[PDB]
Image (tube, coloured by chain):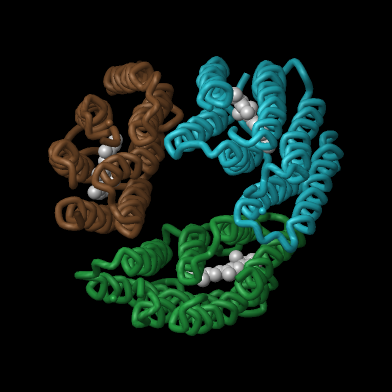
Chain colours: A green, B brown, C cyan
């Protein structure tokens, strides 16, 4: 509690935990294989985030990087490495995407997160932003595929449309927060940055899942 | 050989190596695609464990963690990260599990191992057990799915029943050994802990594989 | 630019980048799901390599290992961990390989790279070569499967034959370069070793992809 941002890490942990438990209870008794995939994917997402928010709260998921002793929460990338592709899989399964398109998405996502991590830990200040730029190019490619790389059922199309729009908006904020926060230019304090990421993460995982798991799009059509 | 536990790391290495070679020879000439998956999965398991037991023997897979300079063999988690999901896949393929259920299993398993590793390396003593608890919750979820989340063929059902029972028993010992050994309360010396893990690992990988690969459950039914 | 090998890391970065962009443009408008998989796989390969060549150029992907202060470019293994299995998947998809065989290949490849990395970072000089030997055994197993573990269409068979022959030749050079270069016996300077790896990598990723993506083997047969 010596670090001002502890409050948002604590709240983040609690909200991911509760979301995980909610999705877990909700998924009880589901027999439809299609719906099972969506529950499995959607429940794992906040469960993973829970563990990484906890690691940050307890101080395990924090390291000091010298550029310009900067506190970098590296645990976010461990979280994102797994949760972002899973979120993309939810969208991909919804629309019955070709395997080729899933691979494209998952691979671009690995690059986005991997280069983001490299940027986060880079000791030469100017180079951090080179990695930011490549990571953003990978994000833009993902956004492109989501709008132009590909829903047959009307309920599938409408849910996909919503979750896709939710994704483009929230995901796009991440590079901006990084850029202006402690990993980037340092204009916004780590405390506020942590709050922004918490709001983003919770919306993109728990908000996302609520929207998805309450839709009948997740069941094969009697 | 300056570390008393070297003998069990040496034996572990030899037993995983021989098991790998046995499974490799045995799988020669197998043409049935189903049986091929089982051999591939079951042979990779001890092959991976071989490499990580070797890394521990030679001292690469050991680090010192300050809490309470504690010797932590981190290589176990590198091994388990890959071998535990593969073992779960063997069981899952056997019963023709839905993809949703496989994802649930694999994901819960990643969490179990990942939080186990975080626990192993955590520098605040009390917090190590928080991570132990979350990892155990993930294990219990796996055990639950194995008994209640789902075999049609009688030979499939019987083999599955055996391998499942083998799994519940041996896997459950792992958290207990951790808790009382050098990663946890330090009641049992690293030397004995290493022996216990060796016996467990060899039974859960080589014993498991022997049981599976001698069964006709692994072939599609003339 | 203080390190003589910077020139080859710079060229490597440029060539992977251009190859990525070429494959990206070329894959535009492709609707055939089969062809989509090949483009996705084949474009991701140099894209990944691009990022890791960049990391090496900027000095992030380099560490000092004490044996015999040896400069080890660890980023190569981060690259190879993902790009080698993807290259094997290209070959595997081409021939419609059984899932069992894909798993065998991917798993053996993970072992090859993982033990290679362990070897690269090992502090006891003699032991480095133990890891080299195990990694090579895994490579030889891959080479075996590629020739004896399994093409129906004549265009599929011919393209596969070429890409397979390209693979056996180039991949086999890697262990030799390691052995004689800075990770191994230190007979050939890091500068020359980096050049050799650059030529190899570019041929095995961009040369490979050119050959594959210009073939009609990648489309399902009007
Ligand atoms: C649950 C977490 C989510 C949905 C996280 C999404 C994160 C991103 C889309 C991050 C993107 C970034 C870049 C595009 C540039 C570099 C910094 C990153 C990693 C924040
Ligand atoms: C071949 C290796 C096997 C089957 C290993 C299984 C290991 C576990 C089930 C470990 C479980 C653990 C917990 C449940 C709590 C924390 C400590 C661990 C990682 C030993
Ligand atoms: C694009 C990169 C490619 C195709 C890299 C292939 C690399 C190898 C086949 C490396 C093999 C190695 C061994 C067999 C022994 C130890 C050293 C390695 C990792 C270079």
Nearest the viewer among B82 and B199 is B82
In screen coordinates, is A95 left or right of C213? left
Q: Is residue A110 above or below residue C86?
A: below
Where residue C7 appears, x then y in whole percent? 86, 39
Q: Residue at x 67, y 16 (%)?
A: C185
Q: Is residue B52 above or below residue C82?
A: above
Q: Is residue C37 above or below residue B57?
A: below
In screen coordinates, is A182 left or right of B143? right
Nearest the viewer among B97 and B123 is B97
In screen coordinates, is B59 left or right of A67? left
- Quadrant of the image containing the C terminus of chain A: bottom left
Visible residue check, residue C155: yes
Visible residue check, residue B69: no
In screen coordinates, is B60 left or right of C140? left
Where residue C63 appears, x then y in whole percent? 65, 38
Nearest the viewer among A70 and C20 is C20
């Amino acid at each position: 509690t010596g670090r001002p941002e502890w409050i948002w890490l604590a709240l983040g942990t609690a909200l991911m935990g509760l979301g995980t438990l909610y999705f877990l209870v909700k998924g009880m008794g589901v027999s439809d294989p299609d719906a099972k995939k969506f529950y499995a994917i959607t429940t794992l997402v906040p469960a993973i985030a829970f563990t990484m928010y906890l690691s940050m709260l307890l101080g395990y998921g924090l390291t000091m990087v010298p550029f310009g002793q900067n506190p970098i929460y590296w645990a976010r990338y461990a979280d994102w490495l797994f949760t972002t592709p899973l979120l993309l899989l939810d969208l991909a399964l919804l629309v019955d995407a070709d395997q080729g398109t899933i691979l494209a998405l998952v691979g671009a996502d690995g690059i986005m997160i991997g280069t983001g991590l490299v940027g986060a830990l880079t000791k030469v200040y100017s180079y951090r932003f080179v990695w930011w730029a490549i990571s953003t190019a990978a994000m833009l490619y993902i956004l492109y595929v989501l709008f132009f790389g590909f829903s047959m059922r009307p309920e599938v199309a409408s849910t996909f449309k919503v979750l896709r729009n939710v994704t483009v908006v929230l995901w796009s904020a991440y590079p901006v927060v990084w850029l202006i926060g402690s990993e980037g230019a340092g204009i916004v304090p780590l405390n506020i940055e942590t709050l922004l990421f918490m709001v983003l993460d919770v919306s993109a995982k728990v908000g996302f899942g609520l929207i998805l798991l309450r839709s009948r799009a997740i069941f094969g059509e009697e």
